[PDB]
Image: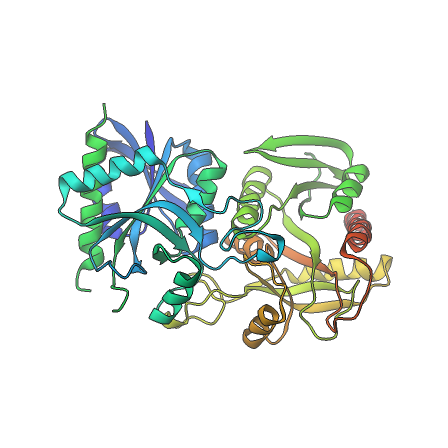
Length: 226
Length: 235
C-alpha cells in the first residue's frame, strides 16, 4: 500500500519526513517528492501548491509518477459552518466548486460541465482518518461538504454568498475539489481534511500545532497497517 | 516523432481536429492516462493534437500530460468563445496577448484582482508564436484580427450581469472562456511558449447572426487551414 499525502502545512511535512525510514527524494517537473516508509506502509509526501490549477498539476504528477493507491490532502481553512470554531476538524464527505456556474445548460450550481456535480471522498479512508483523530486527539470532528475556489474567502459577506448556494458547506478553501477532480479522473480514492483556522464570525502557533497534530494522526494511521 | 519542431494543439472544435488529422502523414493514435493524442507530420513539423477538456482542472491536466509525455516546443490552444469586447462581431479572431482568471480574488493578501497567489497576475502569450499565427490568419483568411486580453473561469458566462461583472474588473477583456488561463498557467510553469486563439461566436451588440452550430463548423475548418499554413511555413 502506497499513500500520497498532498500537504500545505510545513510542520506536517517535517514531522512526516522525520518519521520516515529510508527517505528518497525526487524532484519531478520541479515538484519535490519525499518517499519513505512509515510503519510498514509506503508514503509519498508533496506540497500541493496554491489554487486549483497548481494542486491539479501536483496531483497529476503524484499519481502518474508514483502510482499511489490513495491520496490524503490535509490543510487548514476557515469555517463557513456557523457551529464550527478554530480547532475543529472537518473531514470532507463531498467536495464541490464554490462559484462554478454553468446553470444555463442545466448543470447544478458548482458543477463544471463533464464533471460530476460533487466529488465523493472515499468512505473507508475518511472513516479510518476519523478513527485516528478520535484515538490520538480530543478534537471535535465534523463530516460534511467542503467547497473550493481560486479566491481567498476572507469576509463573512463572501461566506454567506457561498452559503446561499451551499447551505450545508462547512469550509471554503483553494485546493480540495481540484485534487478530488484529478483523483476521481484516475479512479484513486481520496480524503480531504481541514483544520478550522478561524470562526465564521471571526492565531499563535495554530498552523504549527495543527500541522503537528495532523502528522501524529497520519503516523498513527500508517503505523496501524499490516 | 522525428521532426525537430513539435507543436501541441490543445483542441475543442471537431472540424479542426478532423482537418488536422486528415493533413497528417503517418497519423498515430496514442492513449496516455485516458487521453487520446493524435500525432503526426504536417509540412516539416510534428503536431500533437489532444482535446482540452472543459474547465480549468481538466485543461490543466491535459496540458500537464501533453508537456510531460511529448516535450512539445510550444502549445497552441484554439477555440471559439463569445464576445465581451463592445466592437466584436461574429467571425472576429482574438489572438490573446494575455490571459487572466476572471474571478480569482485574493486581494486581501495584496494580490491584483484575478491573481492566484504564487502566480503572475496575468500570463503572457508567446510574442513570436502569436505573431506567426496572426500572419497565417492574414495570409489565408479575411477575418478581422483582434489582439488583447482573454479571461478564464469555471463558469459559463451568459447573462448581461455576468458579463458586466467581468468588465468592471477587466475593462479591456475581449472574451471570457473556460480553459485559456489554466492552459497558460501550466505552460508557463514548464517554460513552454503558448498561444490562445478564439473565434468570436456572437456579436457584442446583440445583433442576430448565424447559429452557433453553423458557425462552429466554419470556425474549425478555418482554424485548421490557418494552422496547416503555419506548420508548412516553419520548414
